[PDB]
Length: 232
Image (cartoon, rainbow, N blue to C red; front, side, top):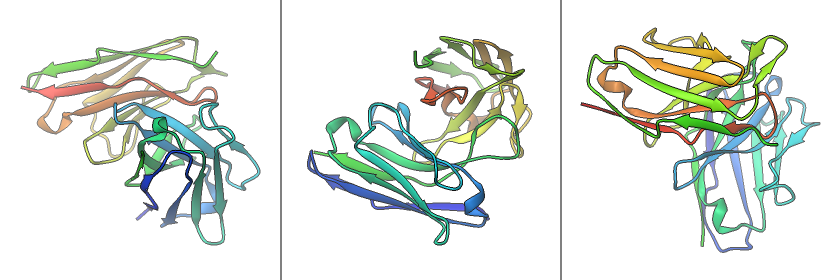
């Protein structure tokens, strides 16, 4: 029932500008913080901007600071990303993502389908292995080593996402250990401080995907490079 529909993607000459829009529905838009998150041609997820529920607070990574402006219209249920001085590195699929409120830890629960842009002491997460092949019925184990603790007041701000090609990421695990509603129990997450594990067992056919870890402990939000999981 909750949906996020992006629009506005396309081709832009370097130096040019572009404005993305996300039409929200099926929820009380004004109650949720929103972000833009992009995925580069190299399949890296990169956080691009966050805006608070009321709009008073906006956050950006240094890579887009001064060039991107996130904004919202709580009357129209619309989220915006105004981009200017666009460069090659900005080439990516851009998703909007809602910050969930059902749990204490910060996480992205709903994502839009994405629109594509073609231009023509940060916490580092070391995820491994980069590539993983498993046989049906076996176990897959994906590891995250964080460059500093992602704990805050007794909780670990570590999330795991699954992404199948052509689709947005999908939350599997939030706060290191907790299974999101609707996710089967053969997925499990573990760890604390700087060491985290995503486990899948027994692996089924439809688990073929790329998996990402993400910390929400500190801005900039950061993701692991990804683990592409192949079957048989």
